[PDB]
Image (cartoon, rainbow over all chains, first blue to last red):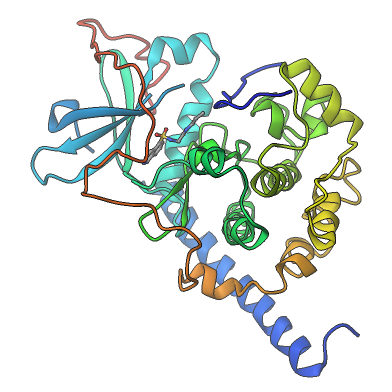
Length: 13
Length: 347
Ligand SMILES: CCCNCCNS(=O)(=O)c1cccc2cnccc12
């Protein structure tokens, strides 16, 4: 199972 | 050895010519970086091409179509992206490469920043990949070669890209790639420290809060090649925290249909140990370009766009958007008061 749609960038963790 | 005399000499000479090309490219980049254009009502807004937003627009005077990125100044400040947004504009205005999207205009108003780019009508690689499932190895290799050359160019200029993924790779009318989305691109001589990128594509050293270098782009290339050839990325889970745990373990499993040459390349790109990762060694980009998986790749022919593309998107007209998904349309509101003027004086 995982993300199949468009993936957004992250600006911080 | 692996190469006979004629082959070794041709390869050596080719590699020296690359150095000569890159030295000239650096001279040209620096001149633009040192001595670097429109307004909103010059364009008709047609349709949203992507959000995160980018709109297809038509220039009123010429009738040319473009992709206009619109950034809300207040949101940029709150998300701590001021410097990143200045980086994107400055880098795009100074670079020049066949696989990098071209910036045509930039401007700002009371509310927004605008970057007007060439419209690439074939759609995102992401769409095509999700629709077909996976690309065959030759098809994936054709795209991968373009990224290798693009990173060879960018890294020679001390530019790190930091957001490789199929969503950011557009297919042009000839079936070649245009890289978009330079919001995380940065001039970096050695190390940098910002935690940014897209979870599935982050190298372990980013997740582990280490100072990291341009080798994060080579890790991301490994993720991209894997995803193109498998249909899904190598570290795959529903939530970011779970993705990060898989990346830092570094255990990678491969589909049974991957060739051994491909698996070898990917083990060397998806390498946690930076002293062993391809693209980060003494031989530089040549460890990648000379790998067996790329043995059929004519690097100059790719650069010259003379290789027949595996896939040519359908195109019905200059403003056609059939290769793009639909998004909710939001009117572009411009406040009567200037927002964040001091923060964006240099834009
Ligand atoms: C997470 C999904 C990210 N997708 C980014 C790439 N697609 S886009 O629509 O924003 C776009 C951006 C920039 C230039 C373009 C030039 N022609 C077409 C589209 C363009």
